[PDB]
Image (cartoon, rainbow, N blue to C red; front, side):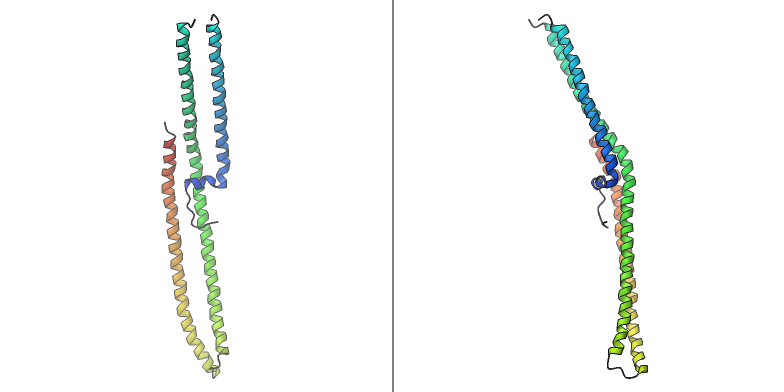
Length: 211
């Protein structure tokens, strides 16, 4: 409900509306980490078979030592594979979500303007109460003031105060109008700064996962 809140990428992530997609993405990846884990035991178990086939005779044969060397680079090649497979998904994760967030950023800022506008118009409404009460209570003062002499006399002074009063409201109404136009402008640009920045923060993230 806050009128000048920075809409950063991290902030965009916390918005309730993105929780559903965020939750889905965390699983999709977790399952793969599980898939990685199975792929490792399966290869690990397969690796073992070779010893039964090869070391049944039992004197360290020259061929076996080379073979075990050959196996190790088959593990580290799958280890290093599983690395890039996760990161590749992480970078691809961002791209799909980024399209969604852009559409959500817009409705977060637009929310800020609608919150401000209804706040502006209410400040307007409050001033008229100040103005309307102000004008009427002054008249009450005319009756209250003893110095009045005649009804024709009472009216004349009221008209004069009625001009001094209106000099204020014209300025007060004009001065307020400027403050609102300025307040919206300084806001409405911050939006188009946070948005020109967002396009290039998403990019900065994808590169971090690039390999």
